[PDB]
Image 1: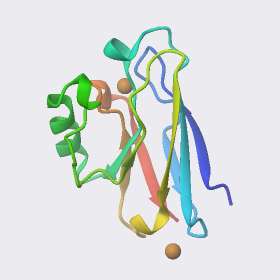
Image 2 (image 1 turned 30 degrees about the vertical axis):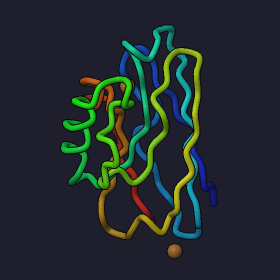
Image 3 (image 1 turned 60 degrees about the vertical axis):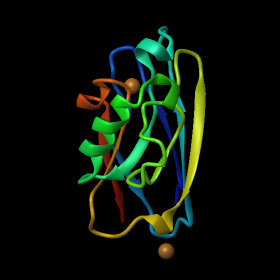
Amino acid sequence: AECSVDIQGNDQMQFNTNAITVDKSCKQFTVNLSHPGNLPKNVMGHNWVLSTAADMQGVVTDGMASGLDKDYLKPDDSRVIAHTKLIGSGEKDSVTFDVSKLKEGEQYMFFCTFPGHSALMKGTLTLK
Ligand SMILES: [Cu+2]
Ligand SMILES: [Cu+2]
């Protein structure tokens, strides 16, 4: 029972991971994000943000409007279950969250909120 995952975000707006499965036995779950690209976060910044598939659009829409200084997230957005900070080339970050915030059945989606990235930088997350 692996309660963690390592993910990368490159210069071609791609996550090296497309689907995450969170085992029910896990009390917590950790995501380790890295950036193997060459570009800084102001132009190729990446974060790993988690929400229900149904809230993704709103989170992305509102986050992109909040600007860089706010890490492309609406301050105190209740639709955000968990998230890493926005990173650039050479940087990294990790996030751990309570698995009790997830439920069976329901589809979750991880994505980057940097302007336009969510088109390709997204994946699925499920509690199974
Ligand atoms: Cu990004
Ligand atoms: Cu439980």
